[PDB]
Every structure is written in C-alpha cells, then in structure tokens.
Image 1 (tube, rainbow, N blue to C red):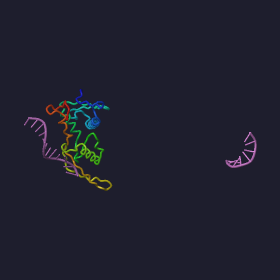
Image 2: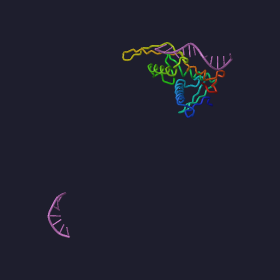
Image 3: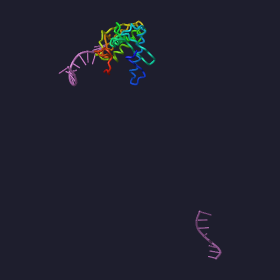
Image 4: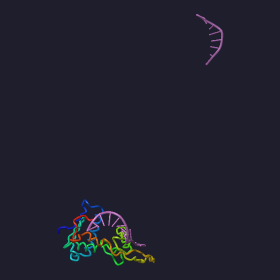
Length: 166
DNA sequence: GTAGATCATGGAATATATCT
C-alpha cells in the first residue's frame, strides 16, 4: 500500500545521525520480525518492507496505536532495571555488558531527569576469579523514549503530525 | 488566557778613468 512513513538513505536532507537512526530502525524491525514473524502479532498490523538502504512502513487503522506498540516493544526495561533494546541481541549479551550499555545511555542520552524516572540502586556481586565485585548501578523505571509517541502523533486525531516537531 | 520569569530536578751593481 501507500507509505505513510517513507525513509531512504539517499535523501539529501538527512545527516549522519539520521542515517544511524535509520540503521537502528532497520535492526529493531529485523529483531521484531524475528520475534513476531506473523502480521497479526504485530500491533496495529504494522508491515515493514526492508531493503539494503530503504525502510518502508505500512499499518492499519489509526497511527497512534501502531507507533505506541512499536515504541513500547522497541524500548523496554528488565527486572534488574537495565536498558532493554530489542535491536541488540540481549540473550547472548552478558549482564556486565548490559550494565555498560545502560550506564552509557543514561549518561549520554538520558542525561536529564526531566526525561526519565529512576528506580532503586541495585547492587550485584558478580564473580570473577573467586572475587565477587559488587556492581552498583541505578535502576530505571520510565523514560521519554517509551512515551515519545504522544509527541509524535497529533493529540486530537491520533495521527502523525503534518508539520515540523520541536 | 498567555508569555516571561522562576523554580524543580536531577545520582551517587757600483765608481772611475778615459774619449770627445
């Protein structure tokens, strides 16, 4: 069907950050079709067509629910409070690297508490060479990434905005 | 009712005789 969202690497207006975000979209949708191969498991019956340098999106019904499902599935938080990005393969990533990436992302992206609410400081004593070093980190509860869908879509029409967004 | 100012909210070589 017609693309409500069209994205190409060859577009002139894009910058480097837009391209790396495009790659992030590509990998998270790859991991989603690995997790949800079938159409009706995908919220809002989203359908993505992926090429070497193009990502293509169609869905059914109102946009708000579709992007809400996409965002909620994309960014998640495990029980330990660490970041859970489906684009990266968390299964074969150990807990130390998970702590590394979570600490990095709160230290560079979520640098401000106006965008995220943190949990309790969770300390775990991981065992290396008969040494239980206590890894101490601040767990999270919510962040603006999980709820950017409200800003992305119009409030009244529950559809994507047709103007520039601050 | 809205725009500007304020406040919260952060993680842990010479002389001499001679010729003319």
